[PDB]
Image 1: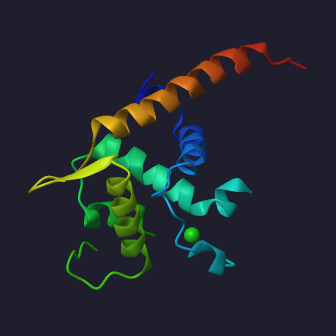
Image 2: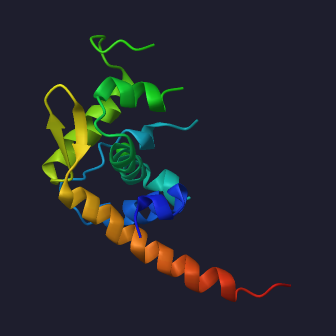
Length: 139
Ligand SMILES: [Cl-]
């Protein structure tokens, strides 16, 4: 299966778990300082997983385009607050892990390693859904 063949939320969950074992993916200790479930406890892993999937889907894609995609105005020169820092750090860690690269004049793209990483996890998830859902009791 590929990323296209599984739901995004469950894929990001499963990718997040696998990213925990990748040494370069190091939570920056930003989310714990916010007061305003695994997706919260493991926020950074989910964030990086989501961004990796977004690069797979949308690449080539630039930092500012990702920032505005995720944000709650395009201004690539402007001094990044929290959202820009998140994209930048995620992309730095993903590049260090070999999963994304920069293409001059194009943006970030997923590498063959990154693509296979996602597609392997998608294949596992697809198999699980195919097994579990049809076998659930009705009532
Ligand atoms: Cl964090």
